[PDB]
Length: 112
Ligand SMILES: [Cl-]
Image (cartoon, rainbow, N blue to C red; front, side):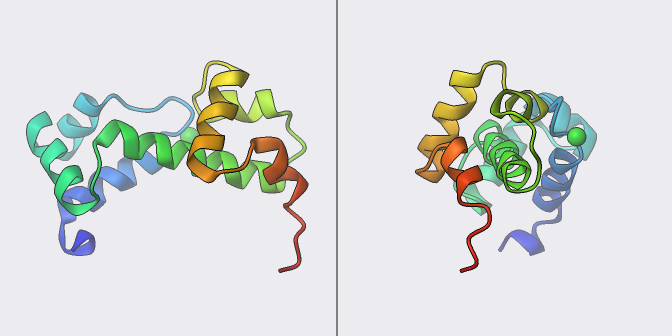
């Protein structure tokens, strides 16, 4: 279970501190003190994915937070979350959340 895997939770905390300019997987591993292979094994075992893909999920969730709370353009938000084009940001966002960034912002005020 992830909370009982301190190395994995450490890596995730480090990733959370580096969203706009994300660390390479190798750099996460160096800073947490495991090999790259070991870091990959942790992510595969305790989260079910690879570190780079979890990092993308994290950056997409920060983007969702910005879509719900700012008037920053779609382009601005994509750049702030490490994306390098609008089409790349919006397409990956839509694949992940099954709505577009524009739809997420339109729906931010949903009162439940
Ligand atoms: Cl950041």
